[PDB]
C-alpha cells in the first residue's frame, strides 16, 4: 500500500471529496478524526470508534509524552499496539526560544518529530508556536515567522528518520492569525518547504463562526490545491459544513466526546441536553434518523437517567451516539459532494439544524 | 416457558448444580448476578454483561424507586425495556414500625412488592428489616420476628397481584444474625409460608470469612433442600467457592464492578491492583487464562495507564474483565460439580488464588 496517496474523486465549488491512501488504511475525505486524548477516545473501545465510521483518530504529543511517556510507548510496541487501533493515527505536535519551548520538560521541532516517531504516528504535525488570537500584525508575523522556521526544522528531522519518511506523512501548519498577509506568507513558506498536507492553525479559539469563515475564505485557496487541507480543532457540525464549503478536507475536535459526557447530544434538528427534564419520559432514540447502535437500542429517557445519575454507561452511550452523528455527517457531506448536491445539502442542513 | 422451575442436575457433598427455568430465560446454578445499580451494570452495555456469561442481573428497589421512580419506569414499559435487558432480573426489596419504615419516603412489605411489581421484576424479594451484626439474642429475634411477619405480608401482597404470581417468583429471606436458634426459627417460619427460593440475609457486613462460613454450616441445611439458596451480598471469589461448598446456589455482589473501577482486577493467582507501577510495562493480559474480550485485546500496561489517567475506557475494561472472571468462576464451579470434582477444584482454586 502507499505511504500517502491523496486523490480527489469529485468537487463542487470549493469543496472536494476523495481519499487518502496510507499503509494502515484508507481515509475518506472530508474526514472527521475523533480525538483520542491519552491513548483512548474517551469512553469508547477502538472497535466502537471504527463502527461509527472513523478511518483515522488523533493522538496528542504533549499528553502522551508526559504519560506514559514516548520511549515507554515505543518499548511496548508503539501507539497502535498499545491502544488497539491498527488504522492511521495523526499526532499533534505538542505545540498547542528559537530552539523550542521549555515547560514546567523540553519541546522543539526536533524532539517533537522524534517523539511522534517513537509513538509511530502515521501523520506527523510540524512543531509550531500558535499565534494567540488577537493579534498585532508585527507580532503575529513574529510568531508566524518562528513557526515557519520551525516547519523547516520539522521537515528536516522527519526526513532524516528514513523509517519515518518511508512510512509516515508530514503536515505543515499555516499561521497568521486573521491577517490575510501573514496567512499568505505562511502559505508560500510552507509550500516552499513542501509537505504531504497543510493545516490551518490558530482558528480554534475565540473567533466566532463568521470571523473563522472569513479567514477561511482567503486562507484555504492559498494552500496547494492538490494536497489535503486540515482545519485544526474545529468543530460544531455547522462549522464543519461551512469549512468544507471553503475547501477543508480534514477535521478534529473534542466537541463530540467532551460535550457528550456533559450530556449534550448532536441531532439533525440541532443539539439537545439530554439532562433536560423534558426527556424524562421520552421513548424516542436520541435522533430519529441516526443509524447508530445507541439509537437502535436506547431511548432518550434511559440515557437521561444514566447521565443525571452520573453513570458511566451514560457517557459511553452519549459519546458513541455523538461520534456516530459526526461520522454520519461526514458521509452525507462526502456523498453529496460526489453527487454534486452539496450546496443543497448545506442549505437543507442549516435550515433543520437551526430550526 | 415455566414461571419458575428449579432442577438440580448434580450434587457433590453440600454443593448442587442445575437450572432455574423462568419465562425470560434459564439461570444456570450456581449463579452470579452482576448488580445493576441504577438500572445499569456499572460501565457495561447489557450485551456485554450477557457476553461475559451472566444469566440474570440484580436491580435495587430502593435506588430505582427514588430515581427515576417506579411508576415512571412502569409507564415507560418496565425495567427490562427501560434498560435493554430482556433476561431475568431479581430486585432486592429496599430493606437493606410494624407497618414498615419511613425515611428521609415510605416502605413496607406491601409497597415493596407493588414497586417490584411496577418494575416488572422476575424474582421478587420479601421485604425485611436486616438484623445488624452484632447482635443480642433477644434483640436479633425481635428484628428477625418482624422480618418473618413481613415475609408473610410480602407473600400475600404478591399473591394478590395475579399478574405477578403467574409470571414472577417470590423469595423469602432468612435472618437471625449468627444465632443458630434464631436462624432455625426463621427457616421454619419461612418454609411454613412457602417461597420459590430462600435467601441467607444478614451475612454481608463485618463478619470475617470464618464466621460467615460457620454460620452457613448450620444455616443452609435448615432451608428446604429443593429450593434455591441465595447468599445476599457475597462476595470475593473465595467466599463464593466456600459458600457453594456449603450449599449456596445464587450470589450477588458489587465487588467485581466497584473494585474494578478502583483498579482491582481478579485473577486465578489472586487479585491485583492494576495501578501498581509494576504493571507499567506488563504486556500480558490481565489474566493469563481468562477467555474475556479484554484479555484477548489489551495488556495490563494499557489498562494500567487508562486507570491512572482516570479514563472511562479503563473502568469499562476492568469491569468487563472482572465480571467475566466471576462468570468464568461460576462455570468452573458448575462443571466441576456436575463432574464430581468440585472438592478438588476448591482445593486447587485456593492454593493458586492464595499463593
Ligand atoms: N499544533 C497546533 N495545534 C492546534 N490546535 C488548534 N490549533 C492549533 C495550532 O495552531 N497548532
Ligand atoms: N434485603 C436484604 N438485602 C441484603 N443485602 C445484604 N444483606 C441483606 C438482607 O439481609 N436483606
Ligand atoms: Zn444515534
Ligand atoms: Zn479477562
Image (tube, coloured by chain):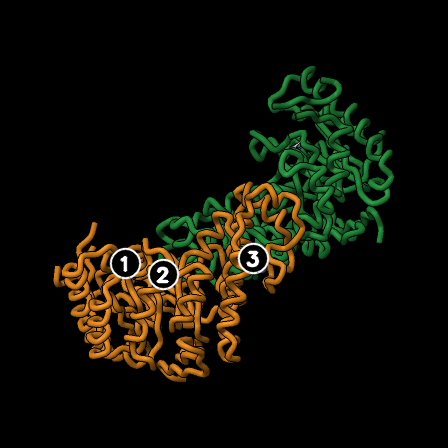
Chain colours: A green, B orange
Q: Are marks 2 and 3 on the same chain?
A: yes
Task: Determine which of the numbered discs, if any, sits on residue B233 in the image.
Answer: 2
Q: Residues within 10 Å of mark 3 (few under 14, many from 20)?
A: some
Q: Are marks 2 and 1 on the same chain?
A: yes
Whether the residue carrying mark 1 lies under 8 Å from ligand 2 is answered with yes
Q: Which residue occupies the foreground of this view, B244 or A135?
A: B244
Looking at the rendered structure, whether the residues under marks 1 and 3 are on a common chain is answered as yes
Cβ of mark 3 under 8 Å from ligand 4: the answer is no
Dot placed on the residue nearer the N-terminal end, 2 or 1: 1
The chain letter for the residue carrying disc 3 is: B
Seen in the image, is B148 located left or right of residue A30? left
* Viewer-nearest of discs 1 and 3: 3
Check the residue under mark 1 and report the chain it is in. B
Judge the density around disc 2: few (<14), some (14-19), many (≥20) Cα neighbours within 10 Å: some
Examine the rendering and report whether any part of residue B20 can be seen: yes
Percent across and percent down for residue B344 are 52, 72
Using the image, determine if residue B188 lies above or below residue B98. Answer: below
Dot 2 lies on which element?
loop
Q: Is mark 2 within 8 Å of ligand 2?
A: yes
Which tag is nearer the camera, tag 2 or tag 1? 2
Residue identifier under label 1: B96
Q: Is residue A272 left or right of residue A199?
A: left
Q: Residue at x 64, y 17 (%)?
A: A136
**Is there CB contact under 8 Å for labels 2 and 1?**
yes
The label shown at residue B269 is 3
The answer for which chain carries disc 2 is: B
Query: Can you see residue A269?
Result: no
Amino acid at each position: 500500500r502507499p505511504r500517502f496517496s491523496f486523490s480527489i474523486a469529485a468537487r463542487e465549488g470549493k469543496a472536494r471529496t476523495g481519499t487518502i491512501e496510507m499503509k494502515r488504511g484508507v481515509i475518506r475525505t472530508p474526514a472527521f478524526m475523533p480525538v483520542g486524548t491519552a491513548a483512548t477516545v474517551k469512553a469508547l473501545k477502538p472497535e466502537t470508534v471504527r463502527a461509527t465510521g472513523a478511518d483515522i483518530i488523533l493522538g496528542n504529543t504533549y499528553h502522551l509524552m508526559l504519560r506514559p511517556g514516548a520511549e515507554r510507548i515505543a518499548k511496548l510496541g508503539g501507539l497502535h499496539s498499545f491502544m488497539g487501533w491498527d488504522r492511521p493515527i495523526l499526532t499533534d505536535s505538542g505545540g498547542y526560544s528559537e530552539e523550542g519551548v521549555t515547560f514546567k520538560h523540553m519541546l522543539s521541532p526536533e524532539r517533537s518529530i522524534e517523539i511522534q516517531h517513537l509513538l509511530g504516528s502515521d501523520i506527523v504535525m510540524a512543531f509550531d508556536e500558535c499565534t494567540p488570537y488577537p493579534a498585532t500584525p508585527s507580532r503575529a508575523a513574529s510568531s508566524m515567522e518562528r513557526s515557519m522556521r520551525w516547519a523547516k526544522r520539522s521537515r528536516d528531522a522527519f526526513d532524516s528518520r528514513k523509517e519515518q519518511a518511508e512510512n509516515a506523512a508530514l503536515f505543515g501548519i499555516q499561521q497568521g492569525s486573521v491577517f490575510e498577509n501573514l496567512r499568505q506568507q505562511s502559505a508560500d513558506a510552507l509550500a516552499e518547504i513542501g509537505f504531504d498536507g497543510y493545516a490551518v492553525g490558530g482558528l480554534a479559539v475565540g473567533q466566532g463562526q463568521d470571523e473563522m469563515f472569513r479567514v477561511l475564505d482567503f486562507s484555504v485557496p492559498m494552500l496547494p490545491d492538490d494536497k489535503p487541507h486540515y482545519l485544526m480543532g474545529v468543530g460544531k457540525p455547522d462549522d464543519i459544513v461551512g469549512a468544507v464549503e471553503r475547501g477543508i478536507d480534514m477535521f478534529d475536535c473534542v466537541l463530540p466526546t467532551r460535550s457528550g459526557r456533559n450530556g449534550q447530544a448532536f441531532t439533525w434538528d440541532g443539539p439537545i441536553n439530554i439532562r433536560n427534564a423534558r426527556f424524562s419520559e421520552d421513548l424516542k432514540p436520541l435522533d430519529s434518523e441516526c443509524h447508530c447502535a445507541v439509537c437502535q437500542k436506547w431511548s432518550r429517557a434511559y440515557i437521561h437517567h444514566l447521565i443525571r445519575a452520573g453513570e458511566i454507561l451514560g457517557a459511553m452511550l452519549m459519546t458513541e451516539h455523538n461520534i456516530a452523528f459526526y461520522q454520519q455527517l461526514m458521509q452525507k457531506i462526502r456523498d453529496s459532494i460526489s453527487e454534486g448536491r452539496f450546496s443543497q445539502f448545506a442549505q437543507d442542513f442549516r435550515a433543520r439544524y437551526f430550526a
